[PDB]
Image 1 (cartoon, rainbow, N blue to C red):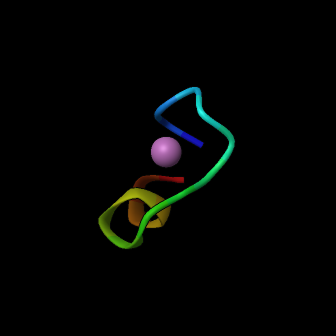
Image 2 (image 1 turned 90 degrees about the vertical axis):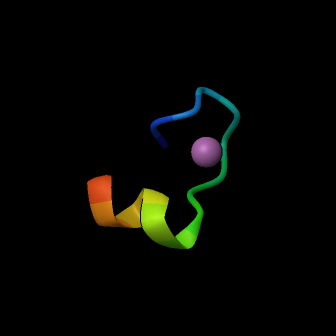
Amino acid sequence: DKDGDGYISAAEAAAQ
Ligand SMILES: [La+3]
């Protein structure tokens, strides 16, 4: 996770 929350969003997973 790149938000330090515990969940990866679409454009997020792209970075995770
Ligand atoms: La996140």
